[PDB]
Image: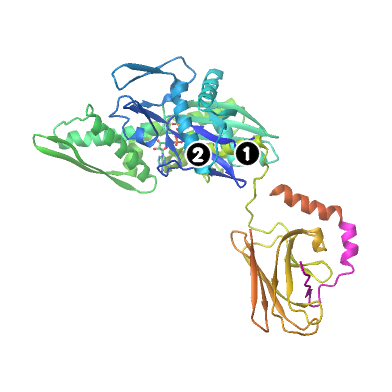
Amino acid sequence: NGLIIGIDLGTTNSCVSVMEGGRPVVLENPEGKRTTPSIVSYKNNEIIVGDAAKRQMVTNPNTIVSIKRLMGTSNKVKVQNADGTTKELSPEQVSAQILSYLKDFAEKKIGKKISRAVITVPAYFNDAERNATKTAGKIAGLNVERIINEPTAAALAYGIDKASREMKVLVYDLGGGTFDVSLLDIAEGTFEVLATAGDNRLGGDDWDNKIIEYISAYIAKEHQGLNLSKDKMAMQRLKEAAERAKIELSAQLETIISLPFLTVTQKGPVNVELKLTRAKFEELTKPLLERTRNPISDVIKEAKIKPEEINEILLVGGSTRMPAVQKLVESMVPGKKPNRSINPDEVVAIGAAIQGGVLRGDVKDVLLLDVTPLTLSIETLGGVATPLIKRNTTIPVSKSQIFSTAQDNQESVDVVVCQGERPMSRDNKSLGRFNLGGIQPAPKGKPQIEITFSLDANGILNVKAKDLTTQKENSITISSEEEIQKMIRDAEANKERDNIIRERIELRNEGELEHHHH
Ligand SMILES: Nc1ncnc2c1ncn2[C@@H]1O[C@H](COP(=O)(O)OP(=O)(O)NP(=O)(O)O)[C@@H](O)[C@H]1O
Ligand SMILES: [Mg+2]
């Protein structure tokens, strides 16, 4: 039936994607963000999800952070109601509020009701943890069409199932809260996790916490041991400044932590303006980073392969944007370049969306080529396909040829554009047509009409026709692996018939364009 959205339900952040026009699109939340914090808060008996919850996660004690850690268990989380009574919530219920929020903004963005999803989980998730996640989906009104592993979703996003060979893929995933490295075997559409190793208390939060310690040490040095660890608002600001500083250090060699009026003492306002260099940050966080190294070696050994047998390495998770992380992974597989070309905080959701598209059976996923797959032609006298841009021409490109009229005293020319390898235009795919009129009366072969086929870097086709005497011109702009193969097959299947046709066709004299009333 309807669309199947792909959901990465992360410990720290969540992300929702869907197939639109044969490409996966990541949907922005109402604050314009492509990921949403996996945080739920409660105030005045109102449920607050995402960015607005994160902004009060220290200051509002009703805030539920890292609920994914309790998924698959019978633990309950307590929150206070407005009246001071206590409410108990299951991990399923809290996760369902995150899913409902994603679902709601997805619906408003797409403009349709959504009732189906593919939801991702860590490779290590057992049945209790997977079933908890499925139940969360059900509570949010989503038929959970499949639960897939996060590294499997990443591999799907990178098209690794299209390799037509056995692929051994290392997926290094460093998120906000968790670290995983999984070794996948991918052959004939089957994904097997050969090994998974990691730490669910090691992620970007821990790097932030080292910056918090650095700021705190500076504060104490500059203000006689001043300690804000029990000041909730100050700690809210420190956590946010620390994450911001870290993110800047992925693109800068230094950053300034700016916290005016962090508190006020008897002596006055405490204003922090503190430099942190990338080098210092890396030194402080070295023990955290180094905890991710041995597990790489461990999964390779578990899978009973050598490092040189790894075909591809994928970087997943927002923390893999850190230069020290990328360099560490590179160091562990000499001669292989880790892939991070798909935004690593979106790649899992993208893979989930791709899986959704597959399960729906839409089969629409288009290609993005830098060379023309099929020949582009104009219809000439007798229904002949006269080529303008030959197949396998690198785009962008413009090609021109001059044509004449097919009949004496012809007033206009039809410009019929077709795609395919067959010699008769009717046997190829019609891409569109237009007419160019105002041609002055003359014998057939006398008028001269310049035809130009132009393909831009985006692969969009502009066909222009200019009468070289009158200077009048008209044009049009023209708006799938299986369809390309179907057309090549049609030519292959009629090769002998078409050769006989071609033997009657001489393209070397000036071509002529007909006009037929419609
Ligand atoms: N440019 C960047 N540089 C450094 N860290 C970043 C960057 N962008 C995002 N992050 C961090 O990436 C982490 C979030 O990763 P993300 O993959 O979105 O979380 P997740 O999928 O919930 N994984 P987990 O928390 O392990 O379940 C946070 O610690 C962010 O601060
Ligand atoms: Mg993720």
| In the rendered image, the vertical position of residue 146 relative to residue 486, given as above or below | above
User: Badge 2 is on which residue?
Assistant: 106
**Residue 176 in the image: x percent, y percent?**
41, 33
Q: Secondary structure at mark 1?
A: helix
Residue numbers of the magenta segment: 495-518
**Is residue 510 rendered magenta in the image?**
yes
The amino acid on which the numbered mark 1 sits, given as a three-letter code, is: Gly
Quarter-of-image position of residue 11 = top left
Quadrant where the image shows the N terminus: top right
User: Badge 1 is on which residue?
Assistant: 357
Residue depicted at 23% across the width and 33% down the height: 234
> Residue 174 vs residue 417: left or right?
left
The amino acid on which the numbered mark 2 sits, given as a three-letter code, is: Ala
Task: Find the distance from the CA under tag 2 to the CA under tag 1.
Answer: 16 Å
Q: Secondary structure at mark 2?
A: helix
Q: Residues within 10 Å of mark 1 (few under 14, many from 20)?
A: many
**Residue 164 in the image: x percent, y percent?**
70, 40
